[PDB]
Image: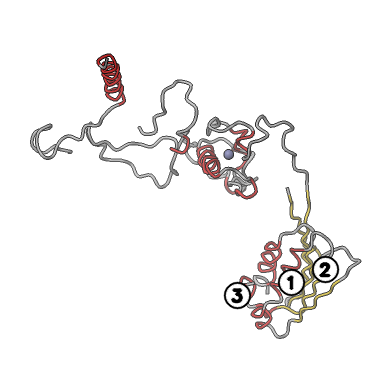
Amino acid sequence: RNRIPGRQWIGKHRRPRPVSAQAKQNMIRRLETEAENQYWLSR
Amino acid sequence: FREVVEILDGKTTIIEGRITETPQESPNPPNPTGQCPICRWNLKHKYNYEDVLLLSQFIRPHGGMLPRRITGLCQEEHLKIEECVKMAHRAGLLPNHRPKLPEGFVPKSKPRLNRYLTRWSPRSVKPIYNKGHRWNKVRMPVGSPLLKDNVSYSGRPLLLYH
Amino acid sequence: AAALARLGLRAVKQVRVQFCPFEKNVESTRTFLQAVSSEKVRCTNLNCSVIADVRHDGSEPCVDVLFGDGHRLIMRGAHLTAQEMLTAFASHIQARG
Ligand SMILES: [Zn+2]
């Protein structure tokens, strides 16, 4: 009774899918790794 | 507590003031420096709708919310105590503070549906017929967002909507 | 004094207010007086006489009213709130008659 016109993930109307707390965790973990990376890449 | 006494005698109506004894505040508050009654007793971000002993200290004999100028609560805490008190009423606690009408305990109704943490009033809610799929969902509110600042011992933040 | 003057005060015979000004608790009765002493209230009934009696020694604020159904209303000011007196006054002196 609710449709997602066309294909789910492609067009100008997409499925709304939300960001989650898990995803935020992962993103931040990976950032922290990069920060530590360029500290050691500096000198 | 000021009781107002009234008499009808010999076609004369007599009205008179009467002062009973109010309890003085407890001897030694943990945060004497503190401003608002919740805070010096160190109860901020702690009480929930479940704590009756705390809520009852602000309300009226017939069940309504007490005014703020008399209580003197930090505005934040006043709205919180309102929502808490309403949830407490709808949760069928404080059965003493319902107003007393004799005709009222006559009319049998299907025994009160036990509910708790109810945000809205029973009347105004409309049954949600449409749900909706994984991506757009209608959510049923539980508890009030005013209480979102309470301490979490689980470390896990509360679910306001389901 | 709106709530009183809106109710058509014409049904009153005599209003006497006895009070003792130097007592710390006076305000309410005084407030009541000034709501009786309003222009519109007094303009409704020209048959109603308002007498203000002041006593230093008495120590008891009191308000007495008479109205046409043969009712004598005595309210004893001690701890009574200002708006309460005007409130009970409206339901007693208007709804009755
Ligand atoms: Zn406070």
Looking at the picture, tell me which residue is in the foreground, C37 or B40: B40
Observer-nearest of A42 and C29 = A42
Q: Are marks 2 and 3 on the same chain?
A: yes
SS for callout 1: helix
Could you say whether the residue bearing mark 3 is in a helix, strand or loop? loop
**In the rendered image, residues at marks 2 and 1 fall on the same chain:** yes
Q: Residues within 10 Å of mark 1 (few under 14, many from 20)?
A: many
- Residue corresponding to mark 3: C6
Identify the coloring. Answer: secondary structure
Chain containing the residue with disc 1: C
**Mark 3 or mark 1, earlier in chain:** 3
Tally of numbered tags:
3
Whether the residues at callouts 3 and 1 have beta carbons within 8 Å, the answer is no
Residue for point 26% across, 16% down: A37
Q: Which mark is residue C79?
A: none
Task: Classify residue B110 as left or right of residue B51.
Answer: left
Q: Are marks 2 and 1 in contact (CB under 8 Å)?
A: yes
Kindly identify the amino acid type of the residue bearing the numbered disc 2: Phe
Rendered image quadrant of residue B143: top left
What residue do we see at 85% from left, 63% from top? Answer: C60
Measured in 3D between alpha carbons, the distance from the residue under mark 3 to the one under mark 1, in whole angstroms, is: 17 Å
Q: Which residue is mark 2?
A: C19
Left or right of B148, for residue B72: right
User: What amino acid type is highlighted by mark number 1?
Assistant: Leu
Nearer to the camera, B146 or B99: B146
Q: Quadrant of the C terminus of chain C?
A: bottom right
Query: Do the residues under discs 2 and 3 have CB atoms within 8 angstroms?
Result: no
Mark 2 and mark 1: Cα distance apart in space: 10 Å
Residue B127 image position (x, y, % from top left): 33, 42
Which residue carries the number 1 mark?
Answer: C33
Q: Earlier in the sequence, mark 2 or mark 1?
A: 2
